Image (spheres, helix red, strand yellow):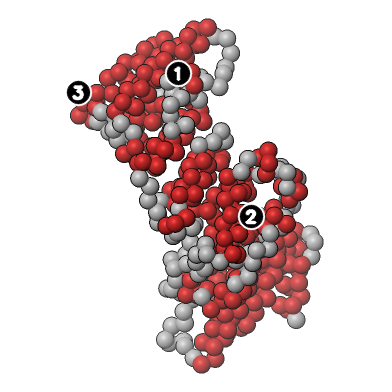
């Protein structure tokens, strides 16, 4: 009755009721013995995860972090292997049964449409596989019966599912297909996987003007998380030779865009994609061609294009050459002259004041093709700008310049 009434507080509406319920659960699992907390771990987990499922979308006072910490403690407690001095026929059986049930419910809630509970379940599975000294797959291999119809959409026309459910399915597919050994192999041969891959490609490659026509996406405020999830799911399929060019094309299209958050998501997915696949300089040039071929005019530069340059350089150091370094130095000199002119004019702040020059300078320390000779012209232009603006302490060019100078200490100090 104690556990019933106390964990029942987790189902009340108010947030303080949930907080008291989780506090009582923590007290019960910390003070009382192991043999008893195991058989109640099912109800404890259910209640303390329903707390999260219900508190999403409303103000709360640290209840989410407290619930996450309590979940971590309960999982590392009940999952801890029993030492030989305490192993017995009843405690071992109770632990095994509680572990089975908890893992079953966790794999069930993994594909839930809520993001917070899904991330919490993923972290719990990871830490549980870490503690038990086993892989996540072998632990989920018996439990994948629940996800036989979840990871494969069964050609359910995901376009009919809501945006949050779609994002949840994408994240579940990414998690289940990115373990040490993959639980489900997206062979891209059955009609189900084929339809799923085609939907992923059309979602991550189409345009917003046509993508917003769907009713499921008509009410979305940003539509960026959906594209991010689509890119993440598409990168997890780096085991299909005959169907790899489209993945690279989509990842590069996402790596060259006029948005910052999506550019970062695309570069992250590419870095994750390169862990299993490889890309030769041929297709690198083929895909970055529209990114280049426009730098001829220094005015064409901007924060987005320099960020894309930085990303493609960080992902492929051997892609750029010394000629590109000289062109970048010329563009930097031009932009520094423009900045000096604008500062002498003293009209008003703009969006091309310092960030562009800082990014262009940082580009050098990431390109290994940058020669030692580039230190002197860069220092000269930096000194010219500093003494034209008379900004010494607040100069934002110090950090990237020092980052580059550290690459050639011999020439620098000389």
Q: Mark 1 or mark 3: which is in front?
A: 1
Residue at (54% x, 36% y) in the render: 257
Q: In this figure, which residue is indicated by the disc labeled 3?
A: 414
- The total of numbered circles placed on residues is 3
Q: Quadrant of the C terminus?
A: top left
Earlier in the chain: of badge 3 and badge 2, it is: 2
Please give the label number shown on residue 297: 1
Q: Is residue 94 left or right of residue 159?
A: left
Can residue 267 be seen here? The reply is yes
* Closer to us: 84 or 387: 387
Asked whether residue 63 is in view, the answer is no
Secondary structure under tag 3 reads loop
- Residue appearing at x 24%, y 23% in the figure: 373
Which image quarter: residue 195? bottom right
Tell me: 139 left or right of 216. left
Q: Position of residue 411 (x, y in %)?
A: 21, 26
Check disc 1: other Cα within 10 Å, few if <14, some if 14-19, many if 20+: few
Q: Position of residue 369 (x, y in %)?
A: 28, 33
Q: Is the residue 121 above or below the residue 356 in the image?
A: below
- 84 versus 267 height, above or below: below
In front: 407, or 66?
A: 407
- Residue at far right of view: 13
Residue placed farthest to the top in the image? 345
Give the distance between the C-alpha atoms of the residues marked 1 and 3, in whole angstroms.
34 Å
Mark in the foreground, 2 or 1: 1
Q: Secondary structure at mark 1?
A: loop
Q: Which residue is mark 2?
A: 167
Residue 173 vertical position relative to residue 399 in the rendered view, above or below: below
Q: Position of residue 143 (x, y in %)?
A: 56, 76
């Amino acid at each position: 009755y104690i556990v019933e009434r106390l964990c029942a507080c987790c189902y009340e509406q108010a947030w303080y009721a949930k907080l008291g319920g989780v506090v009582s659960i923590k007290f019960l699992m910390e003070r009382l013995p192991l043999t008893w907390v195991l058989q109640n771990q099912q109800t404890f987990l259910k209640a303390l995860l329903f707390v999260m499922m219900d508190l999403t979308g409303e103000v709360s006072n640290g209840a989410v972090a407290m619930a996450k910490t309590t979940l971590e403690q309960l999982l590392m407690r009940c999952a801890t292997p029993l030492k030989d001095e305490e192993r017995a026929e009843e405690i071992v059986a109770a632990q095994e049964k509680s572990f089975h049930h908890v893992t079953h419910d966790l794999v069930r809630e993994v594909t839930s449409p809520n993001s917070t509970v899904r991330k919490q379940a993923m972290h719990s599975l990871q830490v549980l596989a870490q503690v038990t000294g086993k892989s996540v797959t072998v632990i989920m291999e018996p439990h994948k019966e629940v996800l036989q119809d979840m990871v494969p959409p069964k050609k359910h026309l995901l376009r009919h599912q809501p945006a949050n459910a779609q994002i949840g399915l994408m994240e579940g597919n990414t998690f289940c297909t990115t373990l040490q050994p993959r639980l489900f192999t997206m062979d891209l041969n059955v009609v189900e996987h084929k339809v799923f891959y085609t939907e992923l490609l059309n979602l991550c490659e189409a345009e917003d003007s046509a993508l917003t026509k769907l009713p499921c996406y008509k009410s979305l405020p940003s539509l960026v998380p959906l594209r991010i999830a689509a890119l993440n799911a598409l990168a997890a399929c780096n085991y299909l030779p005959q169907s790899r060019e489209k993945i690279i094309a989509a990842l590069f299209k996402a790596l060259n865009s006029t948005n910052s958050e999506l550019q970062e998501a695309g570069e992250a997915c590419m870095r994750k994609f390169l862990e299993g696949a490889t890309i030769e300089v041929d297709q690198i040039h083929t895909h970055m061609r529209p990114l280049l071929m426009m730098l001829g005019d220094y005015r064409s530069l901007t924060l987005n294009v320099v960020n894309r340059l930085t990303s493609v350089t960080r992902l492929f150091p051997n892609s750029f050459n010394d000629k590109f370094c000289d062109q970048m130095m010329q563009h930097l000199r031009k932009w520094m002259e423009v900045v000096v002119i604008t500062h002498k004019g003293g009209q008003r702040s703009d969006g091309n004041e310092m960030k562009i020059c800082s990014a262009i300078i940082n580009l050098f320390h990431l390109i290994p093709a940058a020669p030692q000779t580039l230190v002197k012209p860069l220092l000269e232009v930096v000194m010219k700008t500093e003494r034209a603006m008379l900004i010494e302490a607040g100069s934002p060019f110090r950090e990237p310049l020092i980052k580059f100078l550290t690459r050639h200490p011999s020439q620098t100090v000389e």
